Image (cartoon, rainbow, N blue to C red):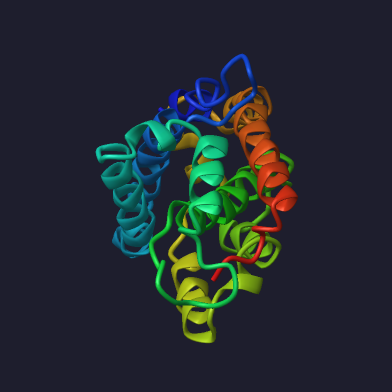
Length: 206
């Protein structure tokens, strides 16, 4: 049931067009749930996305819980209270901003991945579809050892039909429909966030 997760990204944006951290984490746990269902190799990958969702939970359940209500609320609080390492890795290695930025880039990879599938020919290899989207979103931000490790996991990916079928919305061409109809929900929460981070020059936090 991937259709459920891709639309739980509607509740991320409220009326004021702010990204809320609580639906964000909730939808993300839903995406994590979906990755683990691709092999124990992928389960190994998502181990980090989870560790970061915890960092975000641990802040929303703390003294400054109100400040982590939204991303803008977060960026405002942390940037002004000098709680963010802007230059290089140092005193604030688990700040909300640097943490979310990582989730953000990863969310960019998944959206590009699924969108890659949707528009894919029937003969397309999933390993290749994922790699291309990986190279477009994360490759630039990952160490050598990570990149190669990731490259290996890609080869344990199901085939296009099996992967699409695994979305529990029916046959391949039927999920390809759901994709086009549920993808924009995550595509917007991304772009909003990309704006917010680009604004405050937070696009390369260490």
